[PDB]
Image (cartoon, coloured by chain):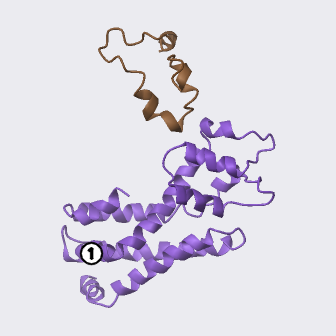
Amino acid sequence: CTGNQQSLAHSRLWDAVVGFLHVFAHMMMKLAQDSSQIELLKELLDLQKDMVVMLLSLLEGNVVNGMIARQMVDMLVESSSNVEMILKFFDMFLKLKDIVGSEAFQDYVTDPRGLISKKDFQKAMDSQKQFTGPEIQFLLSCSEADENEMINFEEFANRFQEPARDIGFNVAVLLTNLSEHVPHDPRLRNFLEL
Amino acid sequence: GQWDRLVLNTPSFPSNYWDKFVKRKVLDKHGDIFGRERIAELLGMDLAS
């Protein structure tokens, strides 16, 4: 409804989403550091689904290098610091699923019932590359507790795959669609390599 | 594809292929993600670690 599309573009809408992007990052980060409030996190992600999808609606039917798509990448620039906080969050839970499962990690686990200690987890993460130190502190913090030696890794990994199987898909579509329509902008490329 | 599993352990693998280091720079790519202490011997080249 192109006549209607320009109305939202010339509207006090971008300053609303950039605020939403800011508040989405911290609670998504704060909520994960607990096991009882996990239930609220699920419907918080559903809000992310219903927010990014409307950005697709603005972008549908657009011309290459158009004016609507220019503000799409432009709005991301001044919100950049908050955006990669969300992007970094998915990386940890999409690579920990790979670390947990490799036989290299199976060396440090010596517990027939299946659990693992805390300090050994810190060593195993540190032994391998990536996962900068402070991130390891965060991953240990969001893990479980009791006896300081009960960390069930087989369940700790499969607690954010199904609930966050979406969102991650609908940001992949968002970045891919933006990359095509505007093909030459160094600001956009910085996010893509993250 | 498996008869050649009998050559990686000897300390003379790069005899003709010019690249007499086809054994140290594989140790570093895979490296950490796999067993660093176990690929140190399955590609021969003991005392590496």
Q: Height in image: A36 above or below B28?
A: below
Depth order, front residue of A130/A165: A130
- Give the residue number, with chain letter if any, for mark 1: A74
Residue A193 lies in quadrant: bottom left
Chain painted brown: B
Type of amino acid under label 1? Asp
How would you rate the neighbour count of disc 1 (Cα within 10 Å): few for under 14, some for 14-19, many for 20 or more? some
Q: Quick one: A44 or A5, which is closer to the camera?
A: A44
Image position, residue A183 (x, y; %): 21, 61
Residue that appears at 68% across and 69% down: A34
> Does A171 sit above or below residue A23?
above
Q: Position of residue B6 (x, y in %)?
A: 51, 10
Residue drawn at 40 percent across, 28 percent down:
B25
Which of A44 and A114 lies nearest the eye of the viewer?
A: A114
Identify by letter the chain in purple.
A
Q: Residue at x 36, y 66 (%)?
A: A174
A66 over B19 or under it: above or below: below
> In the rendered view, does A20 fall on the left or right side of A101?
left
Residue A31 place in picture, x, y as percent? 62, 72
